Length: 186
Image 1 (cartoon, one colour):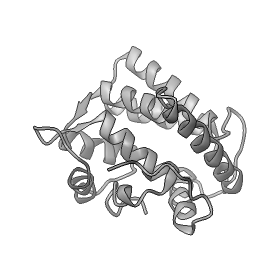
Image 2: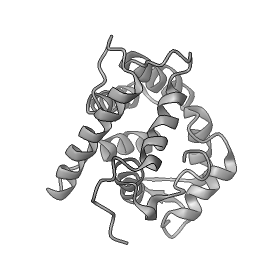
Image 3: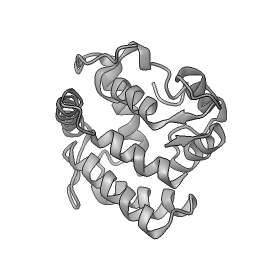
């Protein structure tokens, strides 16, 4: 499949996908999130539970920082959803230009850092990620991810494929990427 490159930023389904994610990040329900919180979730929570090495944690942090700065986040900056979504439009545009240029995207580099903590991850690793990050705590959802994606010869997921899927899921609302997270993310 050719990844869908055209954006669809006014589609209510793309809005809802990021709204779901925003509200998941807004744990205290006050309508605003900060880079501080996102990086703490990355480093203090996820990497600790995954038992990442100090270096892996740092590398992952740098990637999370760059990724979310790309959507307008910053330390001490309290962002509400409309500005966050505007940031995602900018991130998606920038990422697609990199993709066109065959330059690694920030979503790819984040994936590299996640995968390294685990270029392939197993279903059981993905199920753990889903619980620890909280993005997909249902193991059935994680099974759906693996059904959905094109897997390697062992039934494992490669970062190139996950990145293709994430371009379509997070940036372009590619129908080929629908269901990447099962019912865990709309």
